[PDB]
Image 1 (cartoon, each protein chain N blue to C red):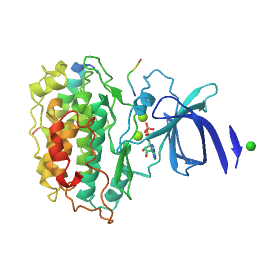
Image 2: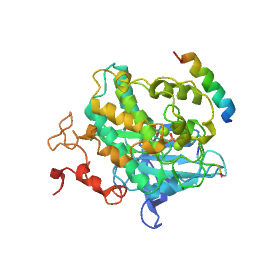
Image 3: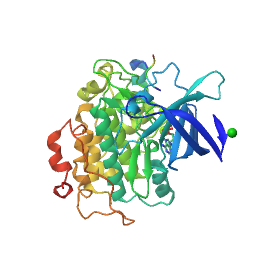
Length: 19
Length: 355
Length: 5
Ligand SMILES: Nc1ncnc2c1ncn2[C@@H]1O[C@H](COP(=O)(O)OP(=O)(O)O)[C@@H](O)[C@H]1O
Ligand SMILES: [Cl-]
Ligand SMILES: [Mg+2]
Ligand SMILES: [Mg+2]
């Protein structure tokens, strides 16, 4: 689980749910 | 050796405690109460005593470090399932060596009891929440005092005797004696119950991951369903952030320093009182927030959790079970399990409990 | 899934 790839997915998910 | 009497299976098995002094053990009434890739789980009746036992049969020769037998042999606690005997036999795979663990049989689990209330659309009464959560923290305090981390805390691993309301922790196939400064596998918990440091791929975690799993169990009991579901680690992490809010840079560094320099969007925290139902006790919410913490060192220790005000009802001298029986043993603390914080015995042992 | 040997 490379941190670069994992962080990108998490940011993309958090942006979608962000107000 | 198998001989007729029902079919009586006779083996020479080693008792869990004391030095290795194997003795003949006879049992019958064998039936499967579980099955998985680990091996097979059987129920049996001991011929001598007639007591029911569970026999977990596994192939303890594999790539993974198999500490299960050695960890269980050291454990002797009223909230941890006892290992009566262990022996070796031939398994389904020919020419292979299978380990057999003979444990006290326990009929139910926290998950099975909880699922009934979910199906019935009721809520698990808070007295059972206090009783079950309190006994789990005692078991965690005991194992953690030896430096052992369960690494698989979840409702399916919490056995119940609904008559006595006694909880027994089990499934030590993932436990490990964590060594400060020795890396560990980061994929060690189960879905919905992995601490955020585990989800971030940390290999330097501690026993506090068990405390996070306990908080997940506690929220699940209060909620009626898992609080952080999700197939993947990102999915579960999104659930956590949506409740706890985006972790700070210092909180991220406490979990895994490799992620400190990423720009995670700031998501506002959802208040705990809005997470659960309006009828939820305030002290349960208070205990939950001190368990589900981003920074692993901020989470309560298991011994500290037992002293929480949410468990004050259990320390009441006139507390009784819903069925009428007196509560199980709750204040018979040994100095071993009180090692981390001996002064907590002032709160842990109520004045009536001392004779 | 214990620690790999
Ligand atoms: N001593 C026991 N008595 C009754 N049921 C048990 C016992 N041990 C395990 N089980 C059942 O077997 C299931 C699997 O748990 P266990 O065998 O301990 O670990 P694993 O899930 O790795 O096989 C649990 O959900 C539990 O209900
Ligand atoms: Cl015979
Ligand atoms: Mg299990
Ligand atoms: Mg296991």
